[PDB]
């Protein structure tokens, strides 16, 4: 609870399981004491010792009378503890960081050519302009037999680069050599720009985000892990399905260890790791974290399986049947679904954008070329300002 | 005015017009508009060459929740079937929407 | 290790100055040739 | 398209009070633990995958 | 695949398989020994590459 440091007793806790425990206590009529598990693990039978840890250990060894907690009903646990009928159902899901905040920069139109090419294009433009002035304008031995002053030279070379032509063309031999070599340069550079832009806009489609849990087994660029001592680790261990077996083999041979002690550590790892690491988790944990800030996450692909949550009791305990009956009654009454909405859907503040799904529409957006419009309007304003200052100077003098 | 409309139309395509600004601020407008049209035309042809390659576009339903919001695609189950009964009793908000 | 199958997905990356370096050499050589030709014609017509 | 809307399976059914219920429940459990269910699922879904 | 594919992909004689591959626009492949493959590859019409 927000005031758990000051509250005492069961008032310190809140959530789906706390409300479910309250409803179960009300229906059956017993008093209950909510206790945090000392081990921290969900539960599994340790190798070569058969000692159950976590929840199953607490239940079997007489430490606890009931476990109203997100426990997945599994066959290997039914042999030592008794579960109630599934009060909620889910499946194994896949967690991965969002593709990218790949928003195009304002000046993203300069991207197809490196900064050095633009710098050297400006330098080559200045050099060609100055040379085309020098070549066409020193004495023929009147001398002004052509219109290629320095300003007209700059205009001609700028027009030649943009492939828009110009009102003049060099008439001497050496002026024509300059024109020809500049024409070849601008042809090569414009073709290269178009070709490279097409290359980017094409290979930006083969991105093909991973899904279906089969891409994880197919490649190893994106690492994935599983909660330690959880039922998902056992699910991957026991399963003989080819894709699940392959992911099991990789995660067993992968180093450093991909396991996380607690689910929160896994969430932090997958959030921080540049989208390189994936987390294998249950669907409800995926869909709740998906709906909570910073909301840097989605849920990808369908559920890997179908396993339900149940309230577990020590084997042979008198609490098993009444609690199971209460769970079934609440399922009939819809209190379980109501609490599901209350704690999953009623805590949402989404959102639901940037899915890059249907939304994604080729039709290149304005944001990709928005810099060109800024340059255009800036140039228009500058031209009006230049005309005004020229008019003022030429009228006042 | 009409000659300038023709020029700025001629400059957007790559067809050289029969006049040129010949002043300083006129040449500034001409130059910046030439750069704009160069970038836009190159983007159009590069994007088209991107699309004519590669396929696997469009999808009507992806999240199984869009059917509750969309109406152009009708959806139904087997009559007197278990799916019909499940929709008939489900209290999930989105499932209740589709059932209604 | 392993390449995935043939994917090798990545950004295209921008053309470096090495890719179009030759056209700049062509251009500057053209400017040098043009200045040489202009001066040759000027000196020929100065005699 | 999309994921599973619900989560429930397919089960062998008998009329209420039929003596056949317990043996067939034992049989389906034995098949599940023997992996025969997976073999039949492969034989009827994945072998004809062309 | 060869056990599940229909119609039968197997051939009675090697020459039948070679003719099948040549006539089948490249949609059919033949499985054969390397040395005998080297001989068919080196004789006309010589459109057969390993
Ligand atoms: C976010 C990206 N999106 N825009 C273009 C781009 C460039 C020009 C125009 N008109 C439209 C779009 C791009 C092209 C690239 C590139 C990076 C980018 C940035 O690296 C290799 O070529
Ligand atoms: N709640 C699971 C932990 C792993 C999982 O999310 O499946 C368990 O009871 O072991």
Image: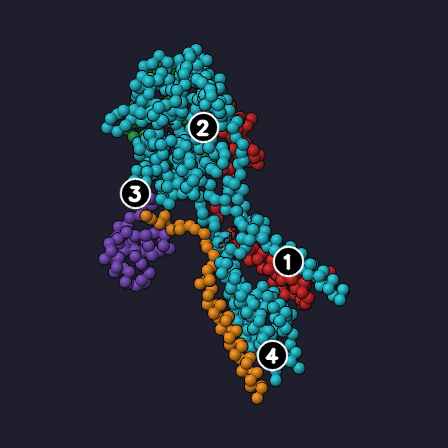
Chain colours: A cyan, B red, C orange, D green, E purple
A233 vs A127, left or right, is left
A141 vs D27, left or right, is right
Report which residue position mark 2 lands on: D6
* Residue occupying image coordinates x 60% and y 66%: A159
Q: Position of residue A119 (x, y in %)?
A: 52, 62
* Residue occupying image coordinates x 52% and y 41%: A354
Marks 2 and 3 sit apart, C-alpha to C-alpha, by 37 Å
* Callout 4 and callout 1 share a chain: yes
Mark drawn on residue E3: 3
Callout 2: residue from which chain?
D
Q: Quadrant of ligand 2?
A: top left
Dot 1 and dot 3 residues touching (CB under 8 Å): no
Report which residue position mark 1 lands on: A379
Of A26 and A245, which appears nearest the observer? A26
Q: Looking at the image, is mark 4 or mark 3 nearer the viewer?
A: 4
Callout 3: residue from which chain?
E
Of E10 and B79, which appears nearest the observer? B79
Q: Position of residue E41 (x, y in %)?
A: 28, 60
State the SS at label 3: loop
Marks 4 and 1 sit apart, C-alpha to C-alpha, by 33 Å
């Amino acid at each position: 609870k927000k005031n758990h440091e000051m509250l005492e007793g069961n008032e310190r806790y809140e959530g789906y399981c706390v409300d479910l425990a309250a409803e179960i206590a009300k229906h059956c009529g017993f008093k209950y004491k909510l206790t945090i598990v000392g081990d921290g693990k969900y539960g599994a039978r340790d190798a070569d010792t058969k000692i159950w840890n976590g929840m199953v250990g607490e239940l079997v060894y007489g430490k606890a009378d009931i476990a109203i907690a997100p426990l997945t009903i599994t066959l290997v646990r039914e042999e030592v503890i008794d579960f109630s009928k599934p009060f909620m159902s889910l499946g194994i899901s896949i967690m991965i960081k969002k593709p990218q905040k790949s928003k195009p920069g304002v000046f993203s139109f300069l991207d197809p050519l490196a900064y050095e090419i633009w710098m050297c294009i400006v330098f080559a433009y200045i050099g060609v302009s100055v040379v085309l002035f020098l070549v066409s304008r020193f004495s023929p031995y009147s001398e002004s037999t052509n219109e290629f002053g320095i300003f007209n030279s700059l205009w001609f070379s700028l027009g030649a680069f943009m492939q828009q032509g110009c009102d003049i063309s060099p008439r001497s031999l050496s002026g024509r050599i300059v024109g020809g070599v500049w024409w070849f340069f601008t042809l090569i550079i414009i073709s290269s720009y178009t070709a490279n832009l097409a290359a980017f806009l094409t290979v930006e489609r083969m991105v093909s985000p991973i899904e279906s849990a089969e891409d994880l087994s197919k490649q190893t660029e994106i690492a994935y892990g599983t909660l330690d001592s959880g039922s998902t680790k056992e699910f991957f261990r026991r399963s003989k399905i080819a894709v699940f077996d392959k992911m099991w083999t990789y995660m067993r041979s992968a180093e450093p260890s991909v396991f996380v002690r607690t689910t929160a550590e896994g969430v932090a790892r997958v959030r921080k790791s540049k989208g390189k690491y994936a987390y294998l988790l249950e669907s409800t944990m995926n869909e709740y974290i998906e709906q909570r800030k910073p909301c840097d996450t989605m849920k990808v692909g369908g559920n890997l399986d179908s396993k339900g949550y149940g309230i577990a009791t020590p084997k042979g305990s008198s609490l098993g049947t009444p609690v199971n009956l209460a769970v079934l009654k609440l399922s009939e009454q819809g209190v379980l679904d109501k609490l599901k909405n209350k704690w999953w859907y009623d805590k949402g503040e989404c959102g639901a954008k940037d899915s890059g799904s249907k939304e994604k529409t080729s039709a290149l957006s304005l944001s990709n070329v928005a810099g060109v419009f800024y340059i255009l309007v800036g140039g228009l304003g500058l031209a009006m300002l230049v005309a005004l200052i020229e008019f003022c100077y030429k009228s006042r003098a």
